[PDB]
RNA sequence: ACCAAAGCUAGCUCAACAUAAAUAAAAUAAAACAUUCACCUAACAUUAAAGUAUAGGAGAUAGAAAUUUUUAUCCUGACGCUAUAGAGAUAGUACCGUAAGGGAAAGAUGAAAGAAUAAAAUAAAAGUAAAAAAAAGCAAAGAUUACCCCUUCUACCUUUUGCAUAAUGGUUUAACCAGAAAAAAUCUAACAAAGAGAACUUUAGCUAGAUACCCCGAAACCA
RNA sequence: GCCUAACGAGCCUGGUGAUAGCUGGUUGUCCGAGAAAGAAUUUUAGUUCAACCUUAAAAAUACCCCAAAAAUUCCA
RNA sequence: UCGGAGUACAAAAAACCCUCCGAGUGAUUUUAAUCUAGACAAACCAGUCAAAAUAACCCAUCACUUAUUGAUCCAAAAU
């Protein structure tokens, strides 16, 4: 349909003159959970312990 | 019954999107944009074909220079490298001819050594 | 009624090919029997089966007499 | 529907197999200097060439 | 000879009953359903229903005149004839639909018959076909039909072929009134288009009788 | 075998969207638009072949036509006034006897032969006769009466030999 | 952001149903032309006979008749199209010609002016913004710097033995605009000595579907 | 010469979308193969079958070809 | 339009407003009756050779050797 492509072209052209600020909560598209992040963090790096301290480390 | 709709306008939009940075109507008008695009692609192919030639010539010039610094010419150095069973490309040889004068000096020394040994064995 | 279908297929004007249609039972076994039967006689076994929703047995030669005799005596 | 050319229908004969037949020309006149064998073989029939036979077939 | 045995479940359609037993022998069944025949039948059924009312005007049918707008040479302009020409924006199209036609064609009887037969086989082996002794709708209300379709877990689209069109008002009245899911049609009016339109088929004993009679007579007429 | 394989798996119920033709059923009609054949639409460069005014068929280009150089005969004269007679083989007849068709003498006639789909329709044939040309007559079945317009010598021979009756009208 | 596009609605085509007189030509086709020419002026229903019987510079083409077969109303619209499409039509007006006659262009705010709600502001054209160190360029690419000089390359199309050619066409942009015919055949399916919905064909045929033959232009002739 | 600003025969409308073998034109992708001359024609700027070519199938064999022989014509 | 000799060197074919000569027939004697294979040449259409069988008897020379003609439809001495 031409309406969806005109709307997509208008949104993509509207984002050029307007730049929205980066948001931390809406950053990731999928749902962000603590356990998912620390799990991947444990799978990537060699060894990871103290999940509570790890979560606390990213807390400000 | 069909319609022209957005098809032609999108094709023109694409061509003009590829026609950016061009000078004059060629970055504006569609036809001149296409005419310039064809030439641009032909020149892309041709220059990408001759790029190896230009780089090769440049490398040959550099190696010729570095060789002439040691008292011998380019062809003699090439021959000596061939009889020395050296398959080293002229790119790396030029890189050594720039950054590492010691290696090229060693190769030139071995070159003059092989040349003098051949000239002494022939006599 | 008449016993079995027999299809004489013409691919071109002067060119002729034989075509059989599935009747009773599965086509594979009968095809194997056709191969084993035509192998000593013809010397080769160029048997090909074309199956969409039904099937077609195609060979190179004219066996149609032996075809009719076989499918008669068998009863299929 | 198509109209068959009568010019072909009169002097040509098509068989059931699609073969065309025509009379040999030249028997009509000036037979005085001609050999009797020539006339004899010109009184018989002859089959048309396939190329022209197809053309005459399309007209019938 | 392979005899197919199909179980006919008799439903008294009041509620909560799936229990019924009748032994049916649908010799109409075919081994492999033909997709090509079905497709050709569908395409044809779509074809003879075309009105072919598309119309336009060729340059000869244009109201405009055939006068030359200017001299051929010396004018400085391009060579041009009447302004009703297709090259002119005041003209029409030459290849246009304007010339009428008929998109239908005559399909062999054996083809369409084998089409309905094969389609019936498709609906049969797909478990979407059910056979009943009769049909009862005492209350005759939409809610009853809906809750019946939901409780008995019938298909999303069910084609009901039962009546001979000459009787049973109580059913037809409720069945033909404001129902998208269920469709009605006489046993003598059963067609392949209607079957392919729905995902589920429900037939009664007389319907199956006349159907198998017609289909056996057509298969026997096509085999002979 | 295909019925069991089609009934075993659960398919999509074959919606109208799942209808597909067999391979090579319908041709992908060629459209002249493209860079495949440039601008001439396969008509070639110029000539009268390009134009829609191209010369009529049956024309040799101005030289004396093929059909005009051919003499005349009465081949076509026949197809008009010829007396039509259709030959029938005794093999077909004995085949009809073997098909379990009507045995007795009395009902047998051309009409019954029409109902048996064993006759040739002659709508464009005026004054249609019926003839019998002998074939497949070896050891054919016996006691069968046949009524035809004019029967050939070997036909009457073959029929009478096995005890059949030839009725000439 | 400027001239600007983008947002709707009149409107109609076609099918069905209801309801004061008197042989016209020619251009053209037969690649010339002369006898000839389906066609058109008024009456002329279906199937089949049949593109047959015949006619024709026996060339192109024209072409029946005898005879055959047929059938009751009631059931309405769109795999037709929108301001360049469909009628020309918001109209035969404005305007042109002495006259006959020829024949156009032309509306959008919002539910409500209650007159600042809208939402993009990108088509060809100039403004915000010009060339820039003694340098060459069918208008770019490889390098190179967030720009350029240097090096590598004889416009497109048409027509032709051959065109960057000082041969042809084009100011640019938008839009409009030019391959629609199945006999025999190849192919996919139905049945098979039969196919095909009372019509034809047939020593594997028959039936159905699917595959190939585009536009503009005269000088003139006739009424 | 003139007959409503151009008369070797006015203009308007209709036949008419007259006729044009000519000239100017004919739009998306990819893959395989791939043509420059035999005789005729009120014909040479056009046609009709050969000289080629392409698609889809079958049955064959074909060429480069030495001495037996008449640059080739034939064949291991 | 056609035939022969060169251009066109040891089977074909091959052009030019290149080059030599010839024909639309002339005459003398015997006379070519029916049809079966199989080939040459050949775009179409026109041109050459001919074993052998049957009925009845028992084509040939010059004009160097070959040329020396005409495909359809339509008319006539009569079939």
Image (cartoon, coloured by chain):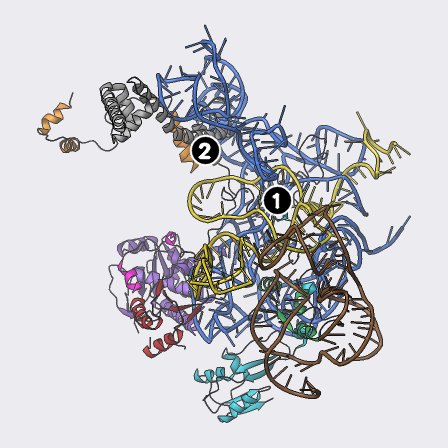
Chain colours: A orange, C red, D green, E purple, F cyan, G blue, H yellow, I brown
Residue E189 visible in this rendered orientation of the protein: no
Q: How many marks?
A: 2
Q: In the image, F7: left or right of E109?
A: left
Q: Between marks 1 and 2, how big is the CA–CA gap?
A: 35 Å
> Which residue is label 2 attached to?
B10
Q: In the image, E219: left or right of E89?
A: left
Q: Chain of mark 2?
A: B
Identify which residue, E181 or G217, lies in the foreground. Answer: G217
Q: Position of residue E202 (x, y in %)?
A: 34, 61
Q: Chain of mark 1?
A: F
Q: Position of residue G45 (x, y in %)?
A: 64, 63
Q: Position of residue E108 (x, y in %)?
A: 48, 65
Residue E85 visible in this rendered orientation of the protein: yes
**The magenta segment:** F1-28
Q: In the image, E200: left or right of H21?
A: left
> Which residue is label 1 attached to?
F46
Residue farthest front in this picture: B123
Identify which residue, C57 or B42, lies in the foreground. Answer: B42
What residue sits 55% from the left and 45% below the top?
F41
Q: Position of residue G150 (x, y in %)?
A: 43, 18
Q: Is label 1 in a helix, a strand or a loop?
A: loop
* Mark 2 nearby-residue class (10 Å; few <14, some 14–19, many ≥20): few
Identify which residue, G79 or I32, lies in the foreground. Answer: I32
Asked where in the image residue H9 lies, by quadrant, the reply is top right
**Image quadrant containing the C terminus of chain E:** bottom left
**Image quadrant containing the N terminus of chain E:** bottom left
């Amino acid at each position: 349909x031409x309406x969806x492509x005109x709307x997509x072209x208008x949104x993509x052209x509207x984002x050029x003159x307007x730049x929205x600020x980066x948001x931390x909560x809406x950053x990731x598209x999928x749902x962000x959970d603590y356990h998912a992040e620390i799990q991947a963090f444990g799978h990537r790096l060699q060894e990871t312990f103290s999940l509570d301290l790890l979560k606390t480390a990213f807390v400000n | 019954l069909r319609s022209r709709v957005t098809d032609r306008y999108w094709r023109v939009q694409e061509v003009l999107k590829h026609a950016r940075h061009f000078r004059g109507r060629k970055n504006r008008c569609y036809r001149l944009a296409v005419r310039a695009v064809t030439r641009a692609f032909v020149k892309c192919t041709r220059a990408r074909r001759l790029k190896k030639r230009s780089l090769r010539t440049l490398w040959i010039n550099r190696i010729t220079a570095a060789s002439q610094e040691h008292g011998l010419k380019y062809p003699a150095f090439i021959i000596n490298l061939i009889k020395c069973q050296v398959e080293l490309n002229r790119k790396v040889l030029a890189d050594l001819a720039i950054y590492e004068p010691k290696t090229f000096k060693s190769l030139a020394a071995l070159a003059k050594r092989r040349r003098x040994x051949x000239x002494x064995x022939x006599x | 009624m008449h016993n079995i279908p027999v299809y004489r297929d013409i691919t071109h004007g002067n060119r002729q090919m034989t075509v059989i249609r599935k009747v009773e039972g599965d086509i594979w076994a009968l095809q194997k029997d056709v191969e084993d039967f035509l192998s000593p006689l013809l010397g080769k076994t160029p048997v090909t089966q074309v199956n969409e929703v039904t099937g077609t047995l195609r060979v190179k030669g004219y066996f149609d007499q032996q075809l009719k005799a076989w499918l008669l005596e068998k009863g299929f | 529907k198509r109209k068959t050319v009568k010019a072909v229908i009169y002097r040509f004969l098509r068989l059931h197999s699609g073969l065309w037949l025509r009379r040999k020309a030249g028997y009509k006149k000036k037979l005085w200097k001609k050999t009797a064998a020539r006339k004899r073989r010109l009184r018989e029939f002859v089959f048309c060439n396939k190329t022209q036979s197809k053309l005459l077939d399309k007209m019938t | 000879x392979x005899x197919x045995x199909x179980x006919x479940x008799x439903x008294x359609x009041x509620x909560x009953x799936x229990x019924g037993l009748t032994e049916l022998h649908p010799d109409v069944f075919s081994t492999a359903p033909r997709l090509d025949i079905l497709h050709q039948v569908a395409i044809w059924q779509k074809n003879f229903k075309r009105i072919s009312y598309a119309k336009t005007k060729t340059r000869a049918e244009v109201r405009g005149g055939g006068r030359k707008p200017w001299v051929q040479k010396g004018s400085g302009r391009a060579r041009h004839g009447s302004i009703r020409s297709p090259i002119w924006r005041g003209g029409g199209v030459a290849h246009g639909p304007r010339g009428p036609t008929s998109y239908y064609y005559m399909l062999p009887m054996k083809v369409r018959v084998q089409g309905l037969k094969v389609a019936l086989t498709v609906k049969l082996a797909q478990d979407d076909l059910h056979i009943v002794d009769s049909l009862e709708l005492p209350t005759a209300d939409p809610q009853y039909l809906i809750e019946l379709a939901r409780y008995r877990r019938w298909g999303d689209s069910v084609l009901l072929v039962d009546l001979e069109h000459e009787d049973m008002p109580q059913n037809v009245v409720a069945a033909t009134s404001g129902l998208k899911t269920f469709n009605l049609v006489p046993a003598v009016g059963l067609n392949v288009h209607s079957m392919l339109k729905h995902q589920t088929l429900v037939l009664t004993l007389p319907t199956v009788a006349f159907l198998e009679e017609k289909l056996x007579x057509x298969x026997x007429x096509x085999x002979x | 075998x295909x019925x069991x394989x089609x009934x075993x798996x659960x398919x999509x119920x074959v919606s109208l969207a799942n209808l597909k033709p067999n391979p090579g059923s319908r041709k992908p009609e060629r459209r002249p638009r493209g860079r495949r054949r440039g601008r001439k639409c396969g008509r070639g460069h110029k000539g009268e072949r390009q134009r829609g005014t191209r010369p009529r068929l049956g024309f040799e280009g101005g030289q004396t036509p093929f059909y005009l150089r051919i003499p005349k005969y009465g081949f076509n004269e026949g197809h008009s006034f010829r007396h039509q007679y259709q030959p029938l083989s005794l093999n077909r007849l004995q085949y009809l006897i073997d098909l379990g068709r009507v045995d007795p003498t009395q009902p047998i006639d051309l009409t019954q032969l029409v109902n048996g789909r064993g006759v040739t329709i002659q709508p464009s044939k005026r004054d249609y006769g019926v003839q019998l040309v002998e074939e497949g007559a070896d050891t054919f079945k016996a006691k069968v009466n046949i009524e035809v317009q004019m029967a050939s010598e070997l036909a009457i021979a073959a029929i009478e030999k096995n005890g059949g009756v030839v009725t000439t009208a």
